[PDB]
Length: 71
Length: 71
Image (cartoon, rainbow over all chains, first blue to last red; front, side):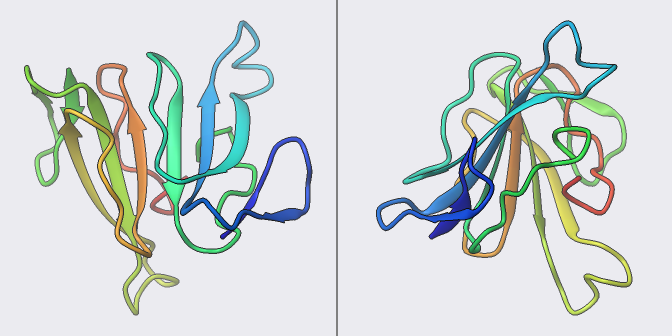
């Protein structure tokens, strides 16, 4: 599967993963900027720590930057 | 944790779950309406079938209707 991977901006091939993921969380700047976001690919929908939020898909290239940083 | 649960519109208490989840997928009407969405609470971030997309959080009430139906 091909997912967008942070920090790169072009879609990467990931032969061993099955989902595309977006992870968003807030810093002191949440309101003025938006959520911080980390884009990747995984074998499985990854585990969240309290306060971080995750989005998982399994369509090629389905993890582009969210806008607000979740939506 | 308290999550929004479909079809109800008021936040429900879920003593045994740890995440709030949003699941979205498309039907023939995707473009004119938006994604179909199912809201719930879980012990863990649930497993996706190809083409369905999932969002998981662990803050009280963090799973309200998405708008577009993912964003």
